[PDB]
Image (cartoon, rainbow over all chains, first blue to last red; front, side):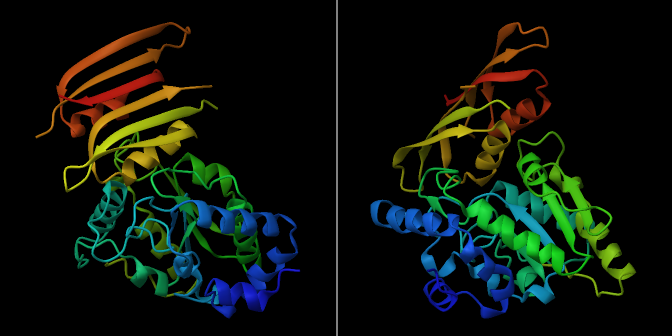
Length: 229
Length: 50
Length: 49
């Protein structure tokens, strides 16, 4: 029933993501997930807008992915979310967790030129896949669309991405990312830390994932990520 | 394994106050929600439900 | 500077509950307070004063 050509046109999905996403259209859950998303869109204010839901497929191809950073659901206020985990639109002052991510980058790289902005498109074009497990949210309600099927769909995309070849870097921040995404640590470079939230047990500014990931890439003869943003 | 309800009374840049209700979250989810909060907190309620 | 009244209902390892009260905290104070809490959180109340 669900046709790839229609699905990618409706959601503005880059066709380079086809081998990784098209098999999800044979999962009967996908039809229920799409009908529930279509129905929520008519009865409530759904974020991010439709053209942004899959912006994460548009910055780089599956073969250009080097690092996977897992998020939960999008920011729930208008103008914040744009389809990438943690990232905010350019005119938006970075919310507290994102400020802590940016401070950890600057502590890792004192010579990095930081803009003070929170738009992470530069990282995304460089193979930093900033992926939320839940792709939509009702305005003003965190995790409101967390049980309609997005995590199963996205879970499928990540599994096929991870299976393509060994050597991905995974940065898993907080309990939720660590419980949901469990890659084989002998196949991929699996990096774990507490969440960047100011409420975490340890200050996120002390996180060295950015340096550890770059030392890993060098051992595989891959050029490092420039973390400046 | 604990689940929580979260209620916030926030104030926007125009001085308008509004409620937000977040239901059945884990304590880790509450911590993520807090780190995404930008408007001024007037009231915050966090209650274990299970 | 916004100051807050912070109330917590906590549960110790023996399953005994107890209240802790904090008056005049900033949001940064609350964050350090929350981060350092080891007992199980039953209730949290943060109110601008």
